[PDB]
Every structure is written in C-alpha cells, then in structure tokens.
Amino acid sequence: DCQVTNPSTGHLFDLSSLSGRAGFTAAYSEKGLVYMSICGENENCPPGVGACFGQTRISVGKANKRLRYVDQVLQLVYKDGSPCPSKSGLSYKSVISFVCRPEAGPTNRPMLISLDKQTCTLFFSWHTPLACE
Picture 1 (tube, one colour):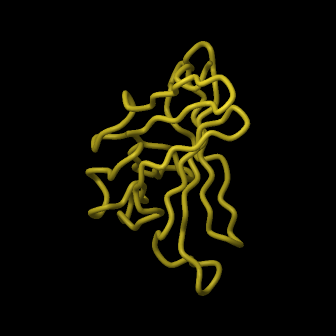
Picture 2 (picture 1 turned 180 degrees about the horizontal axis):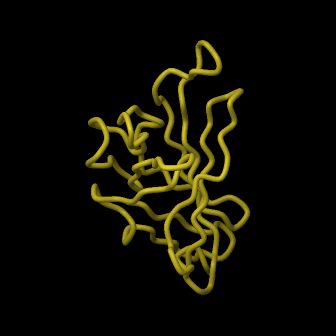
C-alpha cells in the first residue's frame, strides 16, 4: 500500500498521501507533459497505466505498488510501457525516485530528469519531505 521500511532502523515511509488516480504531471520537452500516478493507474492514461505522454496518452509504464528502499531513496519502476522508438524489441519503462527534501519545494511535483534513449527508460525524481527519516 505504497509504503516501505528502512531495513536498518525500522522506519516506515508512507507515500499513500501522493497516491490516487488523479495524480500529477511532469513537464516533458518544451510544451508537453507526462501524466503520472503514484502506486496505481492514472485517470488520464490507458487502463492499468501509471504514466503516459500527455499529447498521445501512450504508455511509459504499467502501474504497480512495489515501493522499494535503496540507499535512502524510495523508488518505483513502472515497466511494460509502449514500444521503444529508439530501440527495437524494448518497451518504455519509468523509474520514479523519491528523495528526502526537509522543506517541500515551491512547486513540489515530480520532474522528468533524463530519458535514456538506448533503453527507453524515463528517470523521474521527486524531492519530498515524505522521504525523510
């Protein structure tokens, strides 16, 4: 249910306050965006899809709720997106990484920071106080 524990302190991280089908957007390119929900599908995307391009609604990853803890970062990986334009045989995937930010940012939305074209992986970051222990 969108929660994970730091194996070494027992601290429970809960990202459920960011969950839900309404979700968020992240800026893509110059005027575009990506629609995304946390730990579940997004209402603007095809059924079961957690993140998709806003212009086309094409999937960049199927939703899941497998939140993981790795070196102080909480992460989700939505795989099995649509066919990769840059490499035959591959499907888009979205990695969403939550990092502690003691004070919430002025905008406070996820950011698409990189798109690895060789593997069609979209890397997103969200610096949030919910990732602080």
